[PDB]
Length: 54
Length: 173
Image (cartoon, rainbow over all chains, first blue to last red; front, side):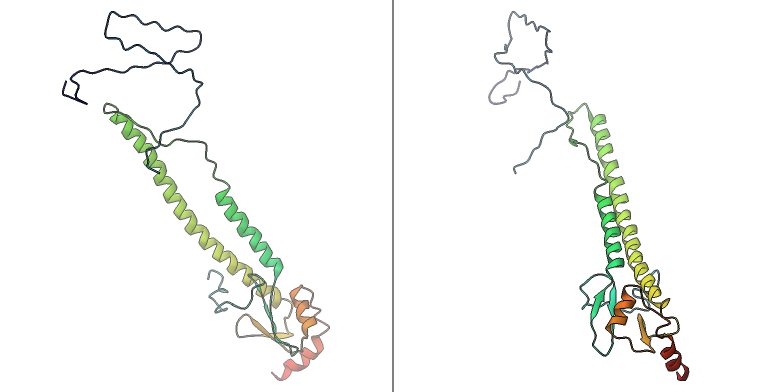
């Protein structure tokens, strides 16, 4: 790939939500960027993001 | 205006009267002065107050995040969101401005009402004991000291008490 931050290679980033009781399973023979820390959160609802210098 | 009292036969306003919106100016020997009619003024303050507090306090607004962000294969969604936002903005702009206009007209007409009704209140008490001089003004045939004026103001006037003197002074006129 064209040099971005001087790097011809890439990492595609992926995420998902794991509800209680359910189990997530990773398997790999290579190219994995494993998780180290995850985020146990409760939801909240109906907000947005602000982009300003105030 | 719509009733011909404010900006109508009453050419202008009284900068010296601070007691309220509606009031009186008397000219009995004892002296002059300005007063306000707190009944009509207070009813008008209650009505207008209720109007404004009804245009404001009636706006329920849930907690809402207007912004939505889309990628480059979601242009249909992005234009749909844009369509929603722009639609509501159009509605509220139009209805808001026309509301302000129409109700401003209504308010001015409401004041014009109150003043004309007040003039008529005074007129129906003084039928033959006075004449309609100039505009928003009555001239008495019998002399009316402060007590009598303050009587016209609070509604009680007592007409037959002054009917005779008036009957005299009116004949030659």
